[PDB]
Image 1 (cartoon, rainbow, N blue to C red):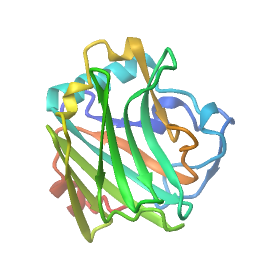
Image 2 (cartoon, rainbow, N blue to C red; image 1 turned 180 degrees about the vertical axis):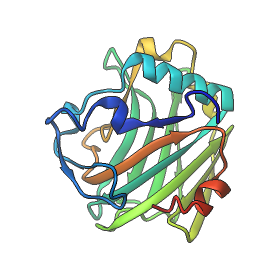
Image 3 (cartoon, rainbow, N blue to C red; image 1 turned 90 degrees about the vertical axis):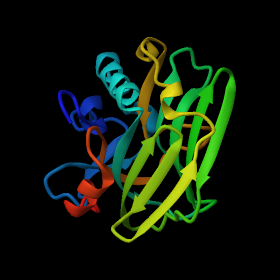
Length: 209
């Protein structure tokens, strides 16, 4: 894309610098840190200014590409990221690797109503490294798992419905944290939003990292 088109969430949080809530370990990418989650509550939020730039990119594109590498404990339901209200009253968006259901769940809360959909046949919690590419556009979600599998789902509302002009003033982006007892268990690496590019381009670059 153009200006501010790649957002690496762990870099933005400063998690690599701050010794709290994780252990730095190896991952598929030999050139970047990987994060074994210990206490997700202690991993800093994305700063407000950075988050508002992300929000504006999503609202502009009417969607996003989200890349992540994960090594998740079997049969666990683990939040990849969530947008949490600063008043502690709940989340407005999350992406959960649901190892209890074998799905990737996408939740949006708009106008007081929670809407959740499962991308089915997306068993990501295997105790082994997996790479995903999630492409959300309008009310459509398409998930590519490693370089072998595509699974799709339809959202009840367009993705941009949640991503408002002043969202950063009322909510924060948290990594690996969400729900009740749904913090991520395992390791994450290279959790990145990418704009102005297609899954086709990512997968040929072998973003099946």
